[PDB]
Image (cartoon, helix red, strand yellow):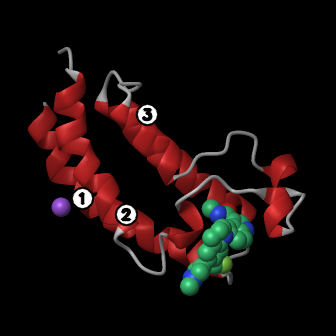
Amino acid sequence: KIFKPEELRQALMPTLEALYRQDPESLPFRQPVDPQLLGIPDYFDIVKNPMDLSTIKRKLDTGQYQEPWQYVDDVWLMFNNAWLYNRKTSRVYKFCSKLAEVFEQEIDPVMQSLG
Ligand SMILES: CNC(=O)c1c[nH]c2ccc(N3CCCc4cc(-c5cnn(C)c5)c(C(F)F)cc43)cc12
Ligand code: NA
């Protein structure tokens, strides 16, 4: 069970695109959180391992995932950082929940088809 890079990209890139297509919900997630620009300096205290869609896309494009679960792990790290940091009434928190619902539905048949 060795996965070729283009096998992972062809299967998994569409699931990432489905997250980017969510508007407005993907908007806080398209680039790394920049705490200084956003006025949230406490972010680097609370979020030890940042992740976002641009980083995941670059890792798929450059062959940094060897197995599918490593990609799923990074998507879930992005979601967990956002639920950890943001208040339950906030846009980014509610938007994260939508992205998780979309991702759950996208990734399920994809994982089957990868073996
Ligand atoms: C994973 N993100 C976090 O953990 C963030 C925690 N604090 C934040 C404050 C602002 C933003 N950013 C980033 C830059 C783009 C952006 C765009 C929107 C947006 C939503 N809709 N529109 C029309 C624009 C929002 C907004 F949801 F707050 C937030 C943000 C992200 C976060
Ligand atoms: Na699709």
Q: Is residue 105 visible?
A: yes
Q: Which circle, 2 or 3, is nearer the viewer?
A: 3
Under circle 1, the secondary element is helix
- The earlier-in-sequence mark between 3 and 1 is 3
Could you tell me the amino acid type at mark 1? Glu
**Disc 2 to disc 1, how far (Cα)?**
9 Å
Residue 15: x, y in percent?
27, 54
Classify residue 17 by image quadrant: bottom left
Quarter placement of the C terminus: top left
Could you tell me the amino acid type at mark 3? Lys
Q: Is residue 88 left or right of residue 1?
A: right
Q: Which residue is mark 3?
A: 59
From this viewpoint, which residue is outermost toward the left?
A: 113
Q: Residue at x 63, y 52 (%)?
A: 32
Q: Is residue 52 above or below residue 67?
A: below
Task: Please rate how many residues cluster around mark 2, counting C-alpha atoms within 10 Å: few if below 14, some from 14 to 19, many from 20.
Answer: many
Q: Which residue is mark 1?
A: 106
